[PDB]
Amino acid sequence: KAGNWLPGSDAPAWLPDDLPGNYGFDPLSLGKEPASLKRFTESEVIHGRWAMLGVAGSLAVELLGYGNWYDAPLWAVNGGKATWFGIEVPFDLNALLAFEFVAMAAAEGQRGDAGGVVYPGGAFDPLGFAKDSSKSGELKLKEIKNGRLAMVAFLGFVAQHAATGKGPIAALGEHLANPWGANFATNGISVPFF
Amino acid sequence: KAGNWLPGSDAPAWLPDDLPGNYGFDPLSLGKEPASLKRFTESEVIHGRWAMLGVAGSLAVELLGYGNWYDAPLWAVNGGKATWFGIEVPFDLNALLAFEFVAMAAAEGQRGDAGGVVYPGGAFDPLGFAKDSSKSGELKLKEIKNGRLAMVAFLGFVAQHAATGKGPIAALGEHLANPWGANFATNGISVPFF
Amino acid sequence: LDPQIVISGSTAAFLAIGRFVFLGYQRREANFDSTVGPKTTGATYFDDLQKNSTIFATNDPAGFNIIDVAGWGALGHAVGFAVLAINSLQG
Amino acid sequence: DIAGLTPCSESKAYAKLEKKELKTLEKRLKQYEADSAPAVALKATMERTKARFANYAKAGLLCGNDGLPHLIADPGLALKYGHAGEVFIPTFGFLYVAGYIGYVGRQYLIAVKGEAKPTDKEIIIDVPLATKLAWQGAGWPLAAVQELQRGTLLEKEENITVSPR
Amino acid sequence: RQSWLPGSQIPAHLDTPAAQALAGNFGFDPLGLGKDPVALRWYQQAELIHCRTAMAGVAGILIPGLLTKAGALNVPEWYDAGKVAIENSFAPWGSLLAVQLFLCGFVEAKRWQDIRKPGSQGEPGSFLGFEASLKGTSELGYPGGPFDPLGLSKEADKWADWKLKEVKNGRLAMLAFLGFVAQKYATGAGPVDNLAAHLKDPWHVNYATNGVSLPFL
Ligand code: CLA
Ligand code: CLA
Ligand code: CLA
Ligand code: CLA
Ligand SMILES: CC1=C[C@H](O)CC(C)(C)[C@H]1/C=C/C(C)=C/C=C/C(C)=C/C=C/C=C(C)/C=C/C=C(C)/C=C/C1=C(C)C[C@H](O)CC1(C)C
Ligand SMILES: CC1=C[C@H](O)CC(C)(C)[C@H]1/C=C/C(C)=C/C=C/C(C)=C/C=C/C=C(C)/C=C/C=C(C)/C=C/C1=C(C)C[C@H](O)CC1(C)C
Ligand SMILES: CC1=C[C@H](O)CC(C)(C)[C@H]1/C=C/C(C)=C/C=C/C(C)=C/C=C/C=C(C)/C=C/C=C(C)/C=C/C1=C(C)C[C@H](O)CC1(C)C
Ligand SMILES: CC1=C(/C=C/C(C)=C/C=C/C(C)=C/C=C/C=C(C)/C=C/C=C(C)/C=C/C2=C(C)CCCC2(C)C)C(C)(C)CCC1
């Protein structure tokens, strides 16, 4: 019980208490069955880790001034060359496609063979946290909460750039310039009848 | 029971459970009788192996740049000479026809004498897989699934080149260029009343 | 374009392919006794121009009579002349 | 066009036949007066005739070398070139009404077999029951496919078969 | 009970505990189609789907149709919405029709297999995990779970009233769409303009005057 998403309302019966991010949030009754609930726990944590990585990446890209996340893949359709922190990358689209396919296929198959495992250990624990399994539960809670936040932020990225076409930090900068003059009601495509 | 091709519906009674690729797929009740079902298992596996070989071959031909699968036999009707990976092949149409007839007749007769056998062993097992007959069942499952996929892909090759006249990789390339602009609704011969 | 090479190689190939691999499958169809062994239970002439009279002896280890030789050689000649005839119309 | 003909609008033979019919009709018209009922009927015939030619030209009909309309009996071809109103729609209309008649009759037969004298109600029609069933089947095809899918449309092999085999 | 025709003999197949437990029963079966309870079951499913898609379609006609007479929402007429949309769009109509055939055929196949077997779609391992919430809710045609998100279908005291409102509005919606079609072929303008031209002059502009809807007078 990290909280309750709606004060007063009763928690659902199928959510077990010992579980990270257990707010009892389920209007649709999607996880009423055991095996499906386990699969959903796996999916939530994994999507969270990938969302964290992507959001941190797009932020780092724009914060260190290398275009947005939308024009990082610009060098492949329009002829050019990739980059990292100010150095060129000598590869072709098919080359990175091949190495990405092989590497990701290998890694995800290897992961997808050990049943459903969410917390590995030993060599995915190289610094020595979460050893006592006591504060590890709290670290699980922090993990899942930051993951939910990251997912929401990334959906924000997709919608925001689908609406105004600008990058995240550019949009934040101009919003801090004139708060009431430009947000999702000056969007002109969010709320139609304005 | 690798699955069920239509959730909810009952499996047919004549399919035995211990069998690779047993999804219970039989609307026409084609395999209700024992001997016919055995013959059909033989045919399915063999067609699968030949389909795998053919599809892999056409993909290799086009991927390494030697024309399509449709213009590999072009050198015999229009005068020319066969090839392999950049080297010429010194034979005549009747020469390869004779050696093909003899070799295939010998091989297929030899195979067609040992009753109906689908998994040989010993000298058609030269690397040492499928020895315990435990994971061999899973390998049978993977075999038959990849075979079904290959048969479907090859029928796709025939139909696709019968419609648009281009090769597989060229068609995929142009489809990745403009997805909505060119597929089997821009075909002009697939769906007539467009 | 030699006729002797095409025809000789053809008949050799077909006699070989009838010798080694299609022998037993041809000899599994010798068993018609399940349905017909008395083609004609007859006594005299007009019945033994219809029943077997002679048996062509083979010291061949597998047992090719002159008849199987005639058959596989005949197919070989048909296919060989087909090859020469398709070669004949100016390639 | 569709098997080597032309539509009747620009068909030369069409207008020639039209002119010929009007010519014979006016020839019959000439010898009467201008108020006579003969002339009234003749002018009515002129109006109906010219209206018929205009109606056949308007519907996009297809004429051969005789200038006569030709019907196209092919689903793909007629539906592709706009001719669904000459065979296709008529066949579905007829099948509707014919199945309707048959279904109403069959329902009457089963309705009267369950009495004490089936022959009297066959020779002397039960008019209330006949009108009732005459209404009750305007949607027959749905009831037909239901009777098919339940297996009551067909008698089993208690039918009398010829003896012997 | 209510009847469509007070004094008319209500047929015996619409007078059962199984048929009176249906939404919007008014004993209306002049052509005796529903003599087979299985057929009545299937036809009820047909009525429900037609109700829901009819409401959706007619709302799509009206609400942009009404709001365009105000300032916002410049929407073209419903019989011309396709053309303009496809000129606005990115793909030809053939590919769109193919994609909707696929994506709708999958779903309709689901629902169909649930009609043939009531507890069908929920059996372990079939889907990737929505098999949890793809069973019925004991009344065929009214699933639960991911449908009805807001939980309105939980209370038992408003149940028959939600049902009955649905079926009544749906029947009215089907009538509305047939009206849209007939007014399109009859007068030749949008339904909102027909409403305006009838309120402007009721005793002169109706289907007794349009010259097509009854030609004998
Ligand atoms: C990546 C998707 C994902 C998945 C699979 C889960 C899975 C889960 N969450 Mg969860 N969650 C997520 C994202 C996700 N979460 C995000 C982003 C947030 C922040 C908003 C939360 C916040 C949250 C809370 C507060 C709680 C859960 C809980 C749960 C568990 C039970 C609920 C359930 O059955 O989930 C099944 C979930 C799905 C099947 C999601 C599938 C996606 C749906 C079908 C479509 C969504 C479309 C979206 C709305 C479109 C937006 C577009 C935009 C333009 C408007 C389950 C393990 C409960 C729990 O105990 O935590 C473990 C709980 O109390 N979640
Ligand atoms: C190519 C090799 C490969 C392989 C073999 C796998 C294998 C696997 N992955 Mg995986 N993955 C890969 C590459 C691969 N991945 C890559 C490159 C990424 C991105 C970095 C991911 C991201 C990823 C996530 C985030 C998750 C997995 C999961 C899984 C497991 C689920 C298996 C399954 O049935 O999914 C079958 C899946 C599909 C057929 C595709 C599903 C498509 C989804 C529903 C559509 C999502 C919306 C779509 C992206 C549009 C978004 C638009 C955007 C603008 C917002 C399995 C072990 C899941 C897991 O572990 O759960 C147990 C999981 O949560 N993977
Ligand atoms: C080479 C053909 C072939 C044959 C002989 C078989 C044989 C068999 N399959 Mg099978 N299968 C095949 C191809 C084949 N498969 C392909 C390509 C797929 C992928 C789509 C599958 C998917 C599949 C499943 C999912 C299942 C089977 C099963 C079976 C077994 C029982 C069904 C039966 O009686 O089959 C008899 C089959 C035939 C007689 C096929 C003959 C070909 C027909 C008569 C004509 C087809 C024309 C085609 C549709 C034209 C397309 C043209 C295009 C332009 C549209 C049997 C051993 C069941 C089983 O237990 O697996 C072992 C089962 O559940 N199959
Ligand atoms: C009584 C038998 C019969 C015959 C001889 C024809 C003859 C014809 N039809 Mg046809 N048709 C029929 C019944 C028949 N139809 C019925 C009952 C239907 C309704 C299902 C159709 C639906 C139909 C369509 C939708 C189309 C044709 C077309 C054609 C023409 C070429 C195709 C063809 O011959 O396929 C051989 C036909 C058969 C062996 C009879 C079975 C009927 C099948 C279902 C029709 C086959 C259509 C074909 C695959 C389309 C080919 C496209 C073409 C460009 C190559 C030809 C004039 C095509 C056309 O317009 O040509 C210009 C076309 O697009 N027909
Ligand atoms: C819970 C629940 C429950 C109840 O019952 C019901 C409901 C409510 C329905 C539900 C809800 C749900 C939800 C909301 C969900 C959401 C999700 C998401 C958002 C995800 C994302 C997710 C997301 C994600 C992962 C993301 C990721 C990202 C990434 C990787 C990125 C990448 C990249 C990079 C490198 C950078 C460059 O430049 C480019 C790119 C390529 C771009
Ligand atoms: C199952 C079932 C059951 C139920 O009951 C009923 C039904 C449904 C009917 C059924 C179904 C069926 C089906 C679908 C089938 C399919 C098949 C196929 C497709 C095959 C292929 C198959 C196919 C195959 C083998 C293929 C093969 C191929 C090949 C070799 C190739 C070759 C080649 C090469 C070297 C290359 C060059 O350049 C040329 C060539 C010469 C070209
Ligand atoms: C009851 C009974 C019983 C007894 O037994 C007998 C009798 C009497 C016969 C019967 C009766 C019947 C009836 C009357 C029926 C009716 C129906 C209907 C009307 C339907 C509709 C129905 C209708 C419907 C669904 C509709 C739908 C619609 C839609 C989707 C729309 C769409 C759209 C839109 C949105 C807009 C865009 O832009 C275009 C479109 C595309 C256009
Ligand atoms: C001694 C010996 C040997 C050898 C053997 C041999 C080599 C044999 C041969 C045999 C032969 C070599 C036979 C042949 C035969 C032939 C034939 C039998 C032919 C026939 C012909 C025909 C049939 C033709 C026909 C025709 C004509 C006339 C023209 C064209 C068309 C036609 C086709 C109709 C060895 C050393 C191995 C060892 C052991 C011992």
Image (spheres, coloured by chain):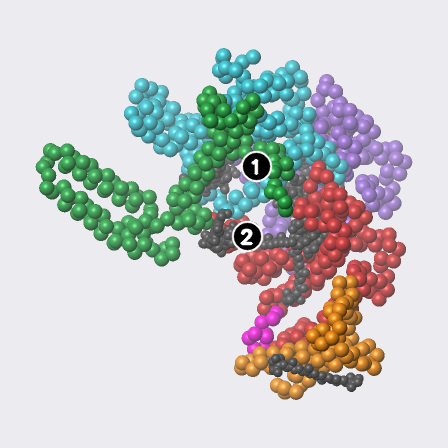
Chain colours: A purple, B red, C orange, D green, E cyan
Nearer-the-camera pick, C9 or D109: D109
- Residue C43 marker: none
Q: Is residue B91 magenta?
A: no
**Does residue D24 appear left or right of residue B39 in this picture?**
left
Q: Nearer the viewer, residue A42 or E123?
A: E123
Circles 1, 2 touching at the beta carbon (< 8 Å): no
Q: Amino acid at mark 1?
A: Glu
Circle 1 residue: A174
Q: CA distance from mark 1 to mark 2?
A: 43 Å
Residue D122 on image: x %, y %: 49, 27
Residue displayed at 84% across by 43% down: A120
Determine if residue E143 is in view.
Answer: yes
User: The numbered mark 2 sits on a residue in which chain?
Assistant: B
**Secondary structure at numbered mark 1:** helix
Q: Secondary structure at mark 2?
A: loop
Q: Is residue A125 left or right of residue C54?
A: right
User: Pointer 2: what residue?
Assistant: B183
Q: Residue at x 80, y 62 (%)?
A: B115
Q: Quadrant of the C terminus of chain E?
A: top left
User: Is disc 2 surrounded by few (<14), some (14 to 19) or many (20+) residues within 10 Å?
Assistant: some
**Which region of the structure is painted magenta?**
B72-80
Instruction: Decide which of A61, D119 is in the foreground and name it.
Output: D119
Query: Subunit of mark 1?
Result: A
Location of residue A184 with respect to B178 vertically, above or below: above
Residue B32 lies, in percent from the top left, at 73, 48
Mark 1 closeness class: few <14, some 14–19, many ≥20 residues within 10 Å: few
Quadrant showing the N terminus of chain E: top right
